[PDB]
Image (cartoon, rainbow, N blue to C red):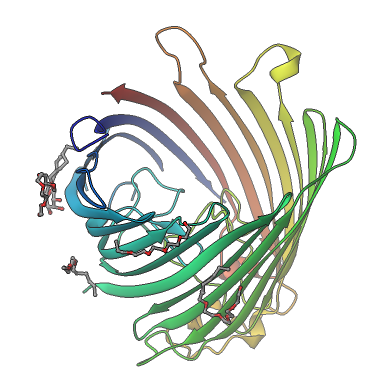
Length: 371
Ligand SMILES: CCCCCCCCOCCOCCOCCOCCO
């Protein structure tokens, strides 16, 4: 289509409300404007992507500082189903993301390469840097791919190096079987290997983390079983934590990722579609985990504070209630409201590591398509 003709600008308005009980509320506006050029015609095309981001409480982006802002752009070059972005850009993959848990995502400065030559295969590579954000600079490079070569099944393999911190490896599989027209099974696994790298700023790291999910769908109902296991004396670690889609036990509050923590969750989801009210969904979860805090090295530079002499039998749990309505028609079409309730308690001195809390979040989201 071409630079002008293929251009699009989106503005995302974000209302964000966060309530915390401890055994502090917060209100914030946010705006994210996104432009994408078309491509100059020819074998090798040229374009531009650019964004700007603002938020205001009603580096530390926002939720704990009265205002925040940022903007950037990247040059894109597209040849043979390969796209190269050079500049500031968003990222989501198993070893790197701006993260979905907070109001504004983090961005990254550098090179990304994405190949779509084969339908069913995505390859990506990259080298970027980023600062520090949410709750000097970092450098990270990754190589990865995602394969779709079978009808109900998907595969991923990724690696990253976070300079002087870690090398991280990740695999996954997801299978879906449709039995009846109303009954389906979704077995799946996530795997993370983590080792220390270079100067080893966080200290020694030898960490293997597993996520198991089994999901029975029946019509609108879906019930899901999760096992998660962290093997090593530091907790599973990743950039921009919370609500991770590469972990089956990542929850509103806790990631159930502590060192040597075994965990499970039972989740229930419902789609109100056939009950007459489409765009309405709800879900509830219960998660339980246990780990032995005596096994942490208290002198571990990055992770030392997980150690507790009195930890031993430490355990915690979380029960999440989640519902969201997207408005599907009229003027507010696409306006989405989402309500989030989490309760978390630990026992066995888990509280020397994390807190007993009750979290309430409300998120109002309005997309605008401007050209
Ligand atoms: C399945 C998508 C292709 C992934 C590109 C390579 C990602 C980098 O991984 C480095 C670590 O991999 C360890 C051994 O890799 C075996 C490579 O061949 C496997 C073929 O799927």
